[PDB]
Amino acid sequence: GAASIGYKRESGARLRTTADMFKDHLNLKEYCPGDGTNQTTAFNAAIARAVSEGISRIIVPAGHYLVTDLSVTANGLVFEGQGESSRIQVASNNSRCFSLSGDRLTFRGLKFIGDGTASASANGIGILAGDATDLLVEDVWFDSFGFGGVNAGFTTLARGPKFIRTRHRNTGTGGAEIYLRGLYEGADVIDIDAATSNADWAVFAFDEGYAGQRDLEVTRGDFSGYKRYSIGVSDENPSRGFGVKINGGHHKNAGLGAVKVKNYRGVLIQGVTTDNCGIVPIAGISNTGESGTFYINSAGLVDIGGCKLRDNGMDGITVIQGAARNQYIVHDNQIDGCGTASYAGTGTGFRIKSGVHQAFLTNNSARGCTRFVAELGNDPSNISETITVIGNDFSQNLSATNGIYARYINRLKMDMNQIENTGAQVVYGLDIDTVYSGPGDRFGNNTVADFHVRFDSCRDLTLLGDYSSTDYTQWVTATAVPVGAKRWNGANAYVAEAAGTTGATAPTHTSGTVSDGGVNWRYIGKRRIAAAAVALRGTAAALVRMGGTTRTNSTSTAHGIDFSPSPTRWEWSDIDAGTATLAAGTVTVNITDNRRQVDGNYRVLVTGTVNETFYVSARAASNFTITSSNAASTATVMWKIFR
Amino acid sequence: AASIGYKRESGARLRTTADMFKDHLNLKEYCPGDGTNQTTAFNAAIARAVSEGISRIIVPAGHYLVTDLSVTANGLVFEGQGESSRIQVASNNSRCFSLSGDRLTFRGLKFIGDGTASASANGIGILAGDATDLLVEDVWFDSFGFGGVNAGFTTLARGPKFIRTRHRNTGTGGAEIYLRGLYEGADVIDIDAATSNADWAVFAFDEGYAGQRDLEVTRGDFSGYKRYSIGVSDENPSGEDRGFGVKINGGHHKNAGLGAVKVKNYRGVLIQGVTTDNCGIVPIAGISNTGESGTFYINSAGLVDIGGCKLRDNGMDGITVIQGAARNQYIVHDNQIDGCGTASYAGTGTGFRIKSGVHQAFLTNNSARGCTRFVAELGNDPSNISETITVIGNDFSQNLSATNGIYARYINRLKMDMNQIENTGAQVVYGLDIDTVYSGPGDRFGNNTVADFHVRFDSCRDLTLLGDYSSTDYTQWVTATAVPVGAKRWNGANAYVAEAAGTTGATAPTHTSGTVSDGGVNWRYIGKRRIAAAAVALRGTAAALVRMGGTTRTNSTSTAHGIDFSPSPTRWEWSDIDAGTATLAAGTVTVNITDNRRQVDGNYRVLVTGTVNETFYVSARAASNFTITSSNAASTATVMWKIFR
Amino acid sequence: GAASIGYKRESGARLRTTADMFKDHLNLKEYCPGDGTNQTTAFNAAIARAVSEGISRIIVPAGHYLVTDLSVTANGLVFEGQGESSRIQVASNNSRCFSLSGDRLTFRGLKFIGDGTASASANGIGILAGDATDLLVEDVWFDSFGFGGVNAGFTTLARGPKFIRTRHRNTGTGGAEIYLRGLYEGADVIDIDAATSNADWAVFAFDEGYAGQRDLEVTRGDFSGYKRYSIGVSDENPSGEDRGFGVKINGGHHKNAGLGAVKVKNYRGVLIQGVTTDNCGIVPIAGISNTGESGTFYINSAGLVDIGGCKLRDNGMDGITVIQGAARNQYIVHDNQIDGCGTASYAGTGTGFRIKSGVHQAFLTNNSARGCTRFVAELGNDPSNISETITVIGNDFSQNLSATNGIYARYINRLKMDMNQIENTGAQVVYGLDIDTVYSGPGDRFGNNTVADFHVRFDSCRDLTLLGDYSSTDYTQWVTATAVPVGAKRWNGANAYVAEAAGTTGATAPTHTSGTVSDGGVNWRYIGKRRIAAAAVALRGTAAALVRMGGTTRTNSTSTAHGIDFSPSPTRWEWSDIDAGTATLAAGTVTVNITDNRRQVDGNYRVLVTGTVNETFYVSARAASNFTITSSNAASTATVMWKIFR
């Protein structure tokens, strides 16, 4: 037949037959009809024929190949489908299409189809791999599998699989689209298209008892609607390599969150964006402290940056340590909404409980939190050592109860932070040995007649920041205001959303935007509602050190000081200074309004300009008197106020 | 051929040679590929593949002239074998394909147009309307009057994927990749885009359709586009649903007319690790002189995070982030500008432009060189007030051509620390109409280029200035002295740095630019020595509070004090100015204030207590000295004093 | 034969022959038997047939094609292998399989095999390229080549190659898997699989005398075992880099590298992000490692350096090294982590951060380092080239017990520091020498020595401002039968400990200087020494012109009560807000005690005081720990307010 029909492209070519042109390759339909019947025996023969002839690629043309648990133990084989019409279906309940042990296998251009049934994480699966190294899975569609697409496990260190542009649909309850087990290096998930209504995970990894290197790098996926996290990554026995890297992708509609990590040595999450994740809490999980669209638990190294997490139904970013030690950096992230699911004990922007790790919170911002914008430490069992806070913006969280909630910390460093119009207490610290809030810090503008900054049973406190209330300019009719200007009326404050001219309807609303007649005013918070700027409770502080940059002004009192258990030593440098001129041998000097004191126990220094003895005869909360030995004194004296 | 039997071995199926062919669909089974108009035959191949249930259509080497090939089915794979698999448009102002089918893919092809176009859906290789999961990979688009692919969407689905697409010779006003409507997961990976006439490489707009519009660009190559390489626009961003916006991850841009990236109203912008060179080099009248300037131009985005971007030889501005009139962070961090204003356009040449309005902005660990206008201008919109801009650890030094290092205006609160600006601007930092200014102890703004103020503030209410605003007191250039490389010496009005270690020659350096050799050492000009008229100056309406401390440096300018308050502040606090102990003689001492802390007047406060039973008082106070006298006209006591405001 | 057998899919299709269906493509086996014989003449005839027929793709089925120096000069060709059994082996020693000069060529799905021999960088190679622009090479395996897989050179600016998922094995002595020469734009190495025992580099690039743009981007490779650096990149004329940035490295994992993972010499731009390494720099080389060149990242004299998000574990020699000799853009090192250093015990070596910036303004932000010998971070330290500005923000260098210095700074003009955390590292936590201006903000914490030495020491520095916490931690004592939470810190003897678990104490005090040992009920981990420092702040060398401290400065709880050890005293010493309070006289005088933490080194400090009544008050005496206030009235019972400062 074909073996007797010679073929020659031109005279200079070899003399071959039309059969030779076909035999250079291996068409699957030389063995399989592709008519939707059970074809496992034919498929197995074609795999074995390629191995026997020394051929790698097996062309899978358009067809329907119903097939059960195919074993391939050879190495170089390429299963090259021509498109989504190259359909490979499971033929039985609770089974799979392929069982892989050969190395350097590659699947391409195929559509795998299941039957929606599964009796194990090793069934209801397109492909089960066991120590199949360097597995390449590219441009393949997994549809209607009871558990997922590929389950790859390893019992000895080797190259992990590469999933490039895999499509996953209709997976069903309790499933993982990609299931990695054991120890591996160089595993990659690139441009995944994951979307379900019932499956738990898109990418799941578990050690399965085996210890050692597990290098996974997920870049640029699309994850939709997974009931547990989109990417689940677990090591139960931490005890070479780095860990997991997540370089981007978009997540939405996830039930618990986008990323969960357990006990991995190193964690690198960069540029990930989520929306409406963690929107279905699970009783028995979400109320046990595990909450957050990022949930990183007991990792040796954590670096999450450039991540934009919007409308989180539960907590935002949660980084927790239990009981190797490396950095916890949370930098350049944004949280837009938190607690949209209205789950109790939930709605926190940043949950950083670092413990032995020295944490770094840098240049983050958060909006729309219902619990704490950032809670730091807060474990009576496991003390967090060092947490330093640089240049964060936790403003405009009117539904939060605390801007920063910090407890059970050894040293808390803060500077350049901006938190306005959030929380009953803007910053609330408890049981912290050493707190430092630099001059660049700004914590103020309450939502409730309470303390801007409160510290309970904290030993060493250095507070140099601006903890005042904003002394807003008042709202007036028929005055020119630019968009961004801030006026106050009654008990509230507002921002202009459009440059214009003031109407006659003075703003009175407590939420949203309302036109005053022409100008649109948006509510931002309350005006000077705080009961005090800096408050102390619990056991007495050993030291409270303030300076010339500390601002406690414009609250309900002139001083903004509320120490109910008084600190054993309260230092305050450069409170006030000036020059006065005596008359009839006396002056009573008025302290500037922003630095009026809580009592008259502050220290005063004074030296005169003439040969007279000057002394401080009285000290009040808002003034002090300087008298001279000359009852007719008219001299000038220079004075200084401090503690 | 249907009668010629074929069998691999005895255990295989008995098939014909025609059966082996019919498993696939060769396009040349219908199209001759000889350069003639073959739309009818091409359509029959497409229609045959759909009826046979075949996805892949193999497109061998050939020349296929084609016009408006409609495909509505979903499985099809148009698989060319390389660049000789040529598909040409066969009509003016038309296209090769019109797709509505989902999961389509094109591979290994070369599309050729005819340089003509009349609308964005003409002069196009492929038009797509609601064609979901479009993959377009390793295909070359050449000579298309408008562009390569136009993909639009009216309902939310998977956006297109363009992998290693090549674009050449497009044409005036064209866009290589047109994106319309709402979509998720759009990807442009490793694009090879270059023109002499086209306007954009990637252009995306809503066309009235609100919703999620997620586009990601990674590691492209963009050269020559007369507008921006990547332009992206939304008109109803409140309806952006469950999306984020635009992400740009790498790639190199060059020779762009206006810039590399333009964004308008997108809810989220992520630009990371992008490098440009010679971008913004062809200004356009009516655009470039209206405030739209900068090789990155981000206008009214809800969230902006650009980092690790290195922008070289910008013809206009560098990075511009502007707000009009949801409210999220503006982070510009770890970026670099090497040069600006190389086109010599008026009102143009600013390194950083951050007008953030309600957005809380962060400027952290950036650096800029070669700026001509401002190195960074913050706020500066009388209409729209910028709330908070905090500036940590930036390097704006060695911009000898800039008029200001930092020009800030119309901000409510400006927080700065750890910044380093030397040898830039007539005024290093110029603030106007700012309510609260904080400059931490790590801030260093000094070494003018003109006899002017290091740090000037106009009509600013609350000023806290704890940084080093001094002039560097360079040591003088000397002959026959060994200098290490990196050493700084002054001669005349100019300061210099050593390019090599060695021993100075005999001819003192007197140049105001470049590097000239003394007899044995090459000296590079770096700026002017102690030329400043003052370190800290105030103008406009009086400041309510000026607060300095023991770290504030105002020394070594033209004056000993470095203060120039033409409207004096209503309150001036300066703690820890000077202190010491003096021992009296004949009942008096006149103490000299330390050189670096000499004052502008004698209105500072003096405290002093004695060592013995005498009354001690301060009888005189001047700008540079003050006297302490005692009751005992023969006093020899030691007194401890302190100077402050 | 085949040309007379008609084929027709259906009535509506063209009537062709079975030969026409084959003549649409070009099967290589139409000219080559693939039987292991020398087939270069046949392979050349196959390539030439594709060119004259206008076909691009040449299908390479499973087979063994022995081949030598195949020249292809045409442009569109695609060499389309079918898998790893598509084997193209070199036929001669010291030779190559291909020599490319054509543009837009692509190789896909092949396995190239060498014979282990090489006599030059252009031999022992799978593919030599010369001005072969727009080269793509994807999913192809290079094995057993004497020098490497691809050597691509360029003499005029054009688009460099793209190596996508290329596998490299068994390259041998002194080779480089990928060799880029000359000037180019848009070169890419994506997802490389690189592993050898004998090769020097995975990716290497140098100018070869051609100045211009040399843009290279590496993304997400796998590198193991290379005797030099995994990625080596070099230029000798950098000023004329034309319209190009430099080299970008965006991830990948390196391991078992001889010298390091990345080397750069004189590139205008360097961008490294997200790279993780393990056990790199483990085979030092005499004549290199002991000449200053050390570090798994070694960036020498680059014009711009931004490295961030990199995690370097178990470095044999040095961590990140950034050096500049003698355009002038930023040096940013941020958000990086060193986990181990100096594991190879090589001399003069073990430093986590080596930053020699010179004219570049350097930034050290939010980095951490552990397990360092030598110095955790050494800044400047070049008697040649002064480092002009280095500013160090929010770094954590704590718990490097085996290091001699946390920070060793030298030959810097201006050193700015704040928000750093360095506890339990070094004989001196921070040691600065020959620095003109030093600033250490109130958020800095440098304390808890490992030697009876100085927490912070400065030699021959001119302007020093120290506002941070340089105290010894005053640990609470370990006591029997007291509940402790995990993370608590107690002391015993000369050592301090931290708890590994909550519970109640035992009855055997911790006496170990390493690791973890149970006391009976709780396991205590050794973390450092207790109050061992001789002084908090020390000054040597030429006298400082100014030492400025403030109310936030901490020098307490060391060996002495003051923490001061100025051997050449500074010409001016300002210390604001040392202490203050109110005293009440008795029999005319009081002697006020300075608080324990702020006890002074002498009685040369200043005192201010004013009284509450009409009496003349003065300070008749001042001692290191106390001063006396007396009045004119020898029966004074008056209250007086005072303040201590310098």
Image (cartoon, coloured by chain):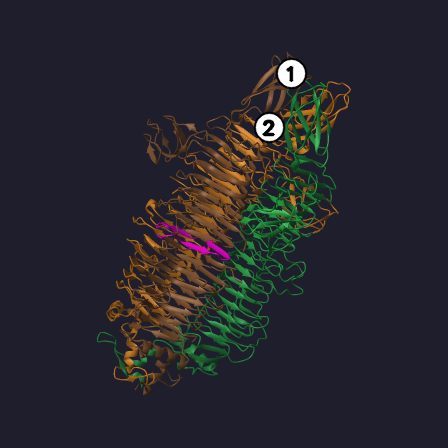
Chain colours: A brown, B orange, C green
Tell me if residue B603 can be seen.
yes
**For residue C295, what is the image quadrant?**
bottom right
Nearer to the camera, B396 or C625: C625
According to the picture, the residue beneath numbered tag 1 turns out to be A628
Q: Residue furthest bottom?
A: A4
Where residue A371 sits, quadrant-wise, is top left
Label 2 secondary element: strand
Residue A293 as seen in the image, left or right of residue C209: left
**What amino acid type should be assigned to the residue bearing mark 1?**
Ser
Q: Is residue A251 above or below residue C571?
A: below
Closer to us: A604 or B381: A604
Percent x, y of residue B618: 68, 22
Coordinates of residue B129 in the picture (x, y in percent)? 28, 57
SS state under label 1: strand
User: What's the amino acid at mark 2?
Assistant: Phe
How crowded pointer 2 is (Cα within 10 Å; few <14, some 14-19, many 20+) is rated as many
Q: Nearer the viewer, residue C387 or A130?
A: A130
* Extent of the magenta region: A253-280
Quadrant in which residue B93 is drawn:
bottom left
Q: Nearer the viewer, residue A486 or C234?
A: A486
Mark 1 Cα shell of 10 Å, populated few (<14), some (14-19), many (≥20): many
Residue topped by disc 2: A642
